[PDB]
Image 1 (cartoon, protein in one colour):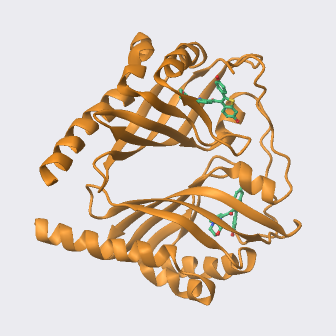
Image 2: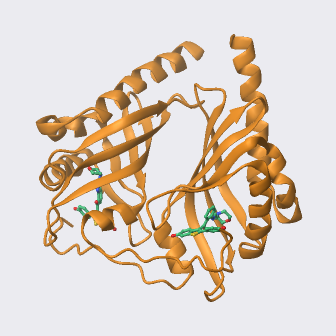
Length: 154
Length: 154
Ligand SMILES: O=C(c1ccccc1NCCN1CCOCC1)c1c(-c2ccc(O)cc2)sc2cc(O)ccc12
Ligand SMILES: O=C(c1ccccc1NCCN1CCOCC1)c1c(-c2ccc(O)cc2)sc2cc(O)ccc12
């Protein structure tokens, strides 16, 4: 069983590496790193609910949208964490690039990110992006509310 | 070398488990799980900058404040991830409890969390909490801005 777990982890790590370094037009084929029923998306949003992209087909459509609205995006400072589960990885990184959201001024978006990658039979079954939405608000020119700190220790 | 790394990982995991299940008055001694120069705090805030608590002494003072403003806090649904670094762990969990911030109505705070734990010589050198601040806004009655989705694929 260890042989099977070790083999899975080494292969899966390569897929995480490839995913995190896919840029430009290659993003339009990255849905092929997912299972047919794979899920990706953003788990930290203004609503408090994830926005999940369900299925390899919808993931490929989302990649077209993402390439338009984040046309020059790069992940940076990438740290890949294997876990005791050979099919579960975490990634800490930063990311930056233009943000071109419908109805908002063109902006520059920078943030810190955590990504979760869960695998099934050599491909990504679930990818989840976690960030601070306040920084995406800022990139869009949306006012960020401020918790009053006057009564808090400083 | 492997024997030392295995031993470190097994000990550090016990510390993560202890940290995540420390409640009530025991929180006032949890700073003793840190190195003398250990750091803890919140990496996801409305300002976009972490709010770090630096040093075991200041972590103990922060615990007094936290016990007042989060008096019944519980971490739930705890998943501890070991990594290839025996001194680096990640935790995915939820959390819930009253929030009693100065000058805000008493509220009920629920959120999803990721925690990073980095260890040095058997104690926590760096703890970092990551969450979606929009849910803390909601718990405090602060209006959360809404990204307009009309132009986005749905
Ligand atoms: O940004 C997204 C998003 C949603 C799902 C999956 C990925 C997303 N972005 C992932 C961005 N990262 C980082 C940059 O480079 C690419 C990867 C949001 C919305 C959205 C909804 C439907 C869509 O068809 C497209 C976008 S609504 C909304 C509201 C918020 O408060 C915050 C974010 C969003
Ligand atoms: O909440 C905190 C906080 C700050 C530092 C360390 C831990 C914190 N909370 C940790 C909460 N978790 C979950 C609940 O149970 C305990 C653990 C925030 C502020 C703060 C500043 C100075 C202080 O002396 C005390 C609090 S300002 C502000 C603004 C925001 O937009 C969001 C959060 C905060």
